[PDB]
Image (cartoon, coloured by chain):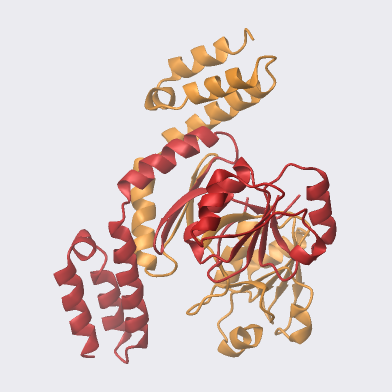
Chain colours: A red, B orange
Amino acid sequence: MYTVMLDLKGRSVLVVGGGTIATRRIKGFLQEGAAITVVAPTVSAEINEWEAKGQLRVKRKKVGEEDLLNVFFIVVATNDQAVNKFVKQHIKNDQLVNMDGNIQIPAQFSRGRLSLAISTDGASPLLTKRIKEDLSSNYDESYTQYTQFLYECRVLIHRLNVSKSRKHELLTEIIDDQYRLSLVKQREFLQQIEKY
Amino acid sequence: MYTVMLDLKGRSVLVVGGGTIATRRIKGFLQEGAAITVVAPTVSAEINEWEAKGQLRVKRKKVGEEDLLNVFFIVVATNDQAVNKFVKIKNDQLVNMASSFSDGNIQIPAQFSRGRLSLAISTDGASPLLTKRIKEDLSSNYDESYTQYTQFLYECRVLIHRLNVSKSRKHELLTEIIDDQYRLSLVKQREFLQQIEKY
């Protein structure tokens, strides 16, 4: 429908539920800057393992209005009809909520600042799974520190008091395999722009 | 940032600005069921046509405090830095700061489609040029064969959903049809359609 990038870095995420969907959702956005709370009577072995590693907070309760305060993003993973109704009746108008609801989560992966998301508008989640695998293979962890390098370069060049002509030159230069796969190449480029 | 589909159906959307960037942004959510209001002293020929077609509302003036009060999603797509700054609203407020350099909490990824297949690519603004490169590289690998194929897959989904056969049979069938040969053989496709008719 309408695909966007959403900043969750440092933001509050509540997951309502603790079964298999809940576990999937959390796996999905763990890398994202967190503040994850899970509210359910019972949770899964996986949520338990994450709770135990300091990755998540759990509240083994029936969700109440006290759980729905100032949460940036709410995920209602559960199917439990009454819980879904309750949450829907107790959130504000502009509440981001994945359930109605106003947030769908597509298959995706990231390599630091790089992200690729795939959908078929529910025609083939199984194709989407295959394409995700193929793309994860083709875009590996080298893109994590490369896109971090790119990001530093963009900020640094932006700040330069150097002509538009030169800025564009510096921004074009750093887009090839040799910048991704050579630390000398990167480090020397950084030495160059530091001098300006 | 994290990738999500935002459902704007029956939500208020404010587009601040009315140039080329505002027009491009609106195109993206024009068929989404939102109530779109566009605020700029002047607006493009295409925004005008959309207004005249009754798909959005136009406010022909510069933005003021009032315009930002009860708006679910704000897109800033102007060129006057004071408008940008002025908009730059509460926290928890969805906003796309399209006109850079700094971000809102909403970014719009590069996207291409092959029929129903959709790919979204972002580098969190690290490099618009890399994003373009990757979109071209993905365009190369996923060509127009995927446009026809997701149409096949869609029809299969429809026909399999209303089969009076088990859930586990449905899954097996929907799994079966995911490989290169289903995509690239029309015989394979057609014989499978015929097969799921018997059930």
Instruction: Count numbered badges in the picture.
Output: 0
Quadrant of residue A35 within the rendered picture: bottom right
Image position, residue B156 (x, y; %): 58, 23
Decide: is B82 above or below A3: below
Q: Give A90 or B2, whichever is nearer the viewer.
A: A90
On screen, residue B42 versus residue A157, left or right, reads right
Q: In the picture provided, is A144 more to the left or to the right than B37?
A: left
- x and y, in percent, of residue B100 in the image: 50, 77
Q: Quadrant of the C terminus of chain A?
A: bottom left
Residue B10 visible somewhere in the drawing: yes
Q: Residue at x 77, y 42 (%)?
A: A80
Q: Position of residue A132 (x, y in %)?
A: 43, 43
Say which of B180 and B168 sits in front.
B168
Classify residue A88 by image quadrant: bottom right
Where, by quadrant of the figure, is residue B181 drawn? top left
Q: Is residue B25 above or below residue A43?
A: below
Above or below, A83 relative to B87: above
Q: Residue drawn at (76%, 61%), measured in percent from left and top? A: B11
Q: Outermost residue, top direction?
A: B198
Tell which of A64 and B114 is nearer to you. Answer: A64
Q: Residue A103: image x %, image y %?
A: 66, 54
Question: Is residue A29 shown to the viewer in this render?
Answer: no
Viewer-proximal residue, A82 or A47?
Answer: A47
Please state if A7 lies on the left or on the right of A66 as rendered. Answer: left
